[PDB]
Image: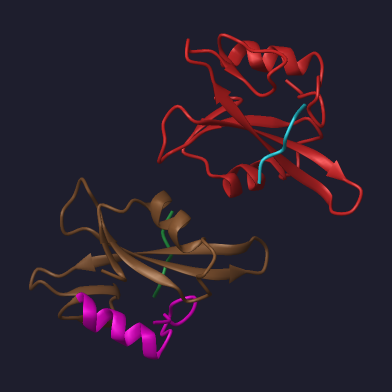
Chain colours: A brown, B red, C cyan, D green
Amino acid sequence: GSWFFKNLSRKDAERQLLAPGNTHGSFLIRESESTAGSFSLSVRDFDQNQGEVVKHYKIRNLDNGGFYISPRITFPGLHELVRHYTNASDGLCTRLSR
Amino acid sequence: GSWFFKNLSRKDAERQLLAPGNTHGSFLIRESESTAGSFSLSVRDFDQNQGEVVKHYKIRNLDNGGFYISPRITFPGLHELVRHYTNASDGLCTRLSR
Amino acid sequence: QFEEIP
Amino acid sequence: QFEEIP
């Protein structure tokens, strides 16, 4: 609805974030169209070698329904995962905006 | 392969063309992901101001199936379009190398 | 964006 | 492809 997109592939996430109006830390969580429940966080950032890049992080699933990018911190849902990284990069290339 | 690429945005072609072993005239035809059948020619060239740049030309579609970049000459296929511009720049910033 | 050709 | 976060 603003940050969550179903059936958004990597390349379509890339054209989306790499579009003007977006800044570093701009992101979206996307669900695979061929594997329901498979989430990926896509983040726009600067890379000293290549310029404006979009980094992809794999959101993993816990058998209890939880999610995590790093095994150091797991979340009950996606909103909790998004709120966390919006207040601290905590391992990520940059903190999320919004 | 070699010169034809599917699912390669403008920025991905530039990064590819601007890489080390490429020279002026190095090119690729890329197919649009959100729009099949919309092609683009991308060539590595030189700008007196910016240095090594990558120029993008839209391939227009003929109703009978052929293509063309300039109204002066049309082709039945992309192989013919490529073979032509590899033997003469004919309006292009440079003759393609391949 | 796209280069024009005569 | 994917980013490695420890």
In this rendering, would B21 be left or right of A84? right
Relative to A35, say whether A57 is above or below: below
Residue B24 magenta = no
Q: How many marks?
A: 0
Is residue B29 at all visible to an observer of this figure?
yes
User: Which residue in the rendered view is the most extreme toward the bottom?
Assistant: A87
The span shown in magenta is A78-98
Image height of A68 relative to A54, above or below: below
Question: Seen in the image, is A26 located left or right of residue B47?
Answer: left
Name above or below for residue C5 compared with residue D2: above
Q: Quadrant of residue B71?
A: top right
Frontmost residue, A64 versus A28:
A28
- The quarter in which the N terminus of chain B is drawn is top right
Image-based side of B25 in relation to A11, left or right: right
Query: Residue A72, can we see it?
Result: no
Q: Residue at x 49, y 75 (%)?
A: A93
Tell whether A3 sits left or right of B7.
left
Residue furthest left in the image: A64
Residue A29: where, in percent of width, then height? 30, 66
Q: Position of residue A67 (x, y in %)?
A: 20, 73
- Image location (x, y in percent) of residue B39: 54, 30
Specify the quadrant that holds the C terminus of chain B: top right
Q: Position of residue B4 (x, y in %)?
A: 56, 26
Answer whether residue A81 is magenta in the image.
yes
Please say if A86 is above or below B61.
below
| Residue at 82 percent of width and 16 percent of height | B88
Furthest residue toward right: B48
Viewer-side residue, B42 vs A69: B42
Q: Residue at x 44, y 59 (%)?
A: A16
Query: Closer to the camera, A87 or B48?
Result: B48
